[PDB]
Image (cartoon, rainbow over all chains, first blue to last red; front, side, top):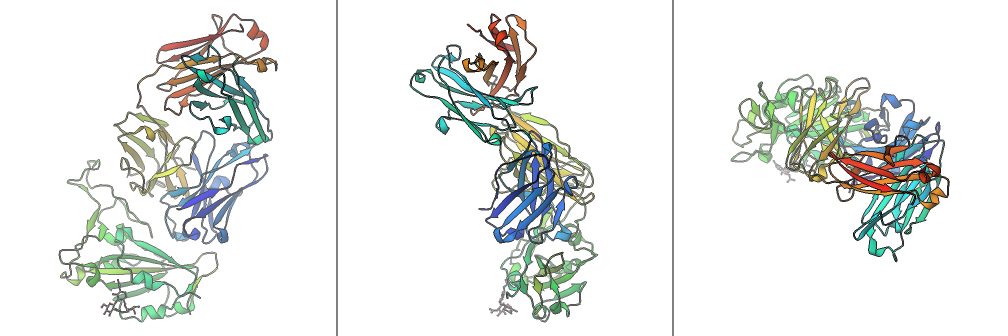
Length: 227
Length: 195
Length: 214
Ligand SMILES: *[C@@H]1O[C@H](CO[C@@H]2O[C@@H](C)[C@@H](O)[C@@H](O)[C@@H]2O)[C@@H](O[C@@H]2O[C@H](CO)[C@@H](O)[C@H](O)[C@H]2NC(C)=O)[C@H](O)[C@H]1NC(C)=O
């Protein structure tokens, strides 16, 4: 199968550069142009440019001309995009996507769309990295209703996004909901994760929320017990 | 050294419909164009922007081979500067075209008693194609003032029509297979050379 | 550079036809073909329509595209709940260097559930948080439909104004909505009020929860 596999998440300081990779497989790399598209949190798609892996030629979006360089290494079917002079609002998911028209003539190019998409690479541009505090939301009488109880974890005062939360190292998935973060007037983020569980389980089942914050290199486990 | 695989293009069992014309890029090979243009198999062999006798002395970044079927009377439309249903709505060459148009009668391959209706062409389009553009869309063509909303009827036409190809047609209505070879020069090393 | 104009939102029920418009200019849609993308929460866009009305393999026949002049439209004929997603149109723009222009995107919601009142769970500040000289009330709102609520915090009977933060509702695993609200405060305030209350209004009716330092 045709696929594009991108490199992993990046955290960079403002003014630094980042280089993201996109490896193609399942087809002949030089047959198709590649596009780069990014998407800032909660916003739309924005085209960055195309590269022709057959020639190395490029066409950059004017907003990024002079700040972005696309390249390729055909020996390993990989395209690269380097963004320099990073700003905080370069924080976004970066996609590579295959131009869907085989064998373009570069001087007579025609765009008909992009048919195969990488999974995306997050790039976060921040000077601060701040780990969260994790507090239990204990199940109680007020949080129990006829056989089911609610319990959770409050993840407070971290920066930047994102944190991921699993329960019981992924063993617990049914009834879990992790909410989006709020941005407080402090500039730090907070979110919560909750799980509905059988109240009959409360005396023997252990509940631990696993809070990952890659930006600060932190993993916090919090055991949540009845009050 | 690889020999360019022109044989695969010219000898394919089936050709594309002209509205959905097929393209192959040819690269990293040596081509003897004399073998091609000194063949008696072709009823059309016209080159633009190059003398065909210098082709064996030139090198290009890539060569493109576009191929499709049209009727004989329409082969004249596969040239820069032409007008007509084919040149306007199916396959358009640029005015600065550098390449060769090669055509041969394919009545024995593409016609059948009863009609071969598998080869289609675009009869209607709201504007001309750009050079080397392809239109494979199948929207109902609104010929009059009333929007068609997907329904066919008067002034609301399916845009593609079938050739009728029967072996007994006169030559003007017989199928011709066409290969358009374009010679590309980019800011990159040449990969297709003469011998 | 140019923009392609889409409505910010659209909706319909299952079995209904929904159309999403995409308005451009003579240098993009007026000159070039239109392609459409579907983006589900948390994943990469997927090509839905290209060359004005062609479907990639695997895209169901209920998705259709059209173009006329400088505008285009995406139709979904027979909405299914899994069609809830963001939709983008795109086209080449011949201006200057030439570039791909994307629409601003359209959020489509599929209203395929009856109204459901929210279940409200209010958590007082945890002992550990108070033992860090901080306090947060956490109001968790689950299992409601459609996805619009307002949240009021009350200190005793008095409205509470400052230190509230509320999330925009989003889908739970079971395709109902959840939302969350936070009231931050100092431990002294928490200890000095008979109660606190989170009241959630969903479609004109209010569900209330109350907690106290007792
Ligand atoms: C595909 O090609 C064969 C062979 O054509 C010959 O070999 C080529 C490499 C080239 O040298 C041609 O000029 C040759 O004629 C075609 O088969 C021939 O068909 C003709 C029909 O008139 C017949 O007289 C020949 O005897 C056939 N040759 C052989 C070796 O059998 C065949 O028709 C081509 N197929 C298509 C789809 O075009």
